[PDB]
Amino acid sequence: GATKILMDSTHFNEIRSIIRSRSVAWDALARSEELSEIDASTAKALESILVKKVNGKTLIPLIHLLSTSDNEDCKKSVQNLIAELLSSDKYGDDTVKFFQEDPKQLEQLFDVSLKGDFQTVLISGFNVVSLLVQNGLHNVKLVEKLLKNNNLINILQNIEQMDTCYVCIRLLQELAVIPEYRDVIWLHEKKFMPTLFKILQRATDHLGIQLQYHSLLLIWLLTFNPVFANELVQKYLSDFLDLLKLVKITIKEKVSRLCISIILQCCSTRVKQHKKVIKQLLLLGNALPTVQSLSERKYSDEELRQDISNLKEILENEYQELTSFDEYVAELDSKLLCWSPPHVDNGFWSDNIDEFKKDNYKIFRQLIELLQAKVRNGDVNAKQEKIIIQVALNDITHVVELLPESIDVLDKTGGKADIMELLNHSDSRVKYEALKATQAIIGYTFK
Image (cartoon, rainbow, N blue to C red; front, side):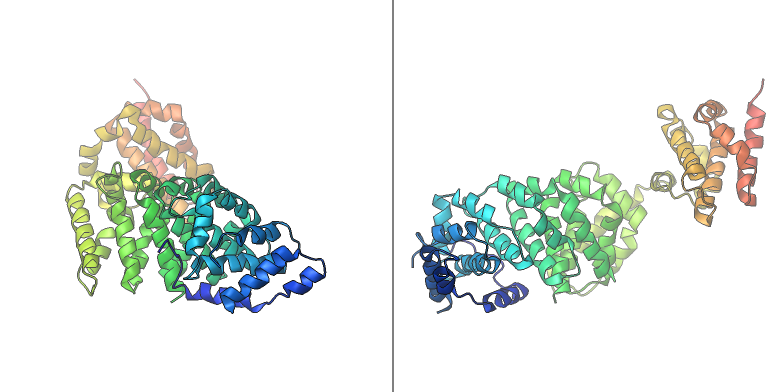
């Protein structure tokens, strides 16, 4: 036909049912002078036609009313009838045309749309979108608008009401289908994105298995642009890496796929310096193991295995090209210094030193910053906070003894000192590391 979105949605269909339940007595309303027959009569008529008329001079009054009205329960049944048309197998075909020809009508409806009772807002949305993504009704400004509209966004944010939240998302996602829209949307990822993920932890541990998907999908869609992909990954990282978690724990295979895919999309030849990404997956999210395990399994859905198989390869290769230093960075970058062979490996040090003495030892300074942070930042001795330190005093030390000329930067940055007081500690290892870190410098402070 001409696009009847959300046709299988049972929870929508269900929401729909709770709205058409509340009946309106036009006539009376008319008669009571609460409406204008014209309208009132026109709807009362439609209402039957639908629930028991080409479409042309039917809307106009509706909208009118819609616009001109204070009967929240009225506009509802209307907003709805509007919807009922849109999907009506019979109508809903011309319904579009109506706007196809008067794309402002759509502008107008739009104003009367998205308001009041949570449902009113939905169907309204529902309707409005049904059109926005229409044959040739594309109208980002509107999208742009609804994207910033509250009422609906709010609906979308509250995860507690799955049915709705659910819908919204599906709406949003239907728009994302519209390449053009894609930019607008992403532009406000800040509103749906978070939600999407909250929706994913919850999952990570049919309706709730649709939401998951739909949200993926929405993602997967936009993600399609190297940059967008670029962005997500290095902004919604933590969660990113999580996909896997669900990727794992999950079934049906309609989700995984999405995950797996998103993931790849994000390592696509196209995402700039996917490399990091691969690194990250491998490095920061244990992609590998995780994938290896999936790689071999029950995937009635071929392509699924495929994709999985494919991911497998990527990871694997990049892996080989893995130097211990990377690991180094990973911890440094991620701000999580550990205790790992390389750390205490003069050899690791003996080869990756230069790397610290880079662009003005960026890396070192980096190293240093971090340490500096932990000190004030939070100012906690909780194992963690308390570890990074030594680890830092440690790496720092090494660098120190190796590149004696590194002392300056130390001097400049402040750590040089920072350390010194670090000796006045609570935890041995810390003052200690710091100590071992200071007796080192001591040697290079003179002649």
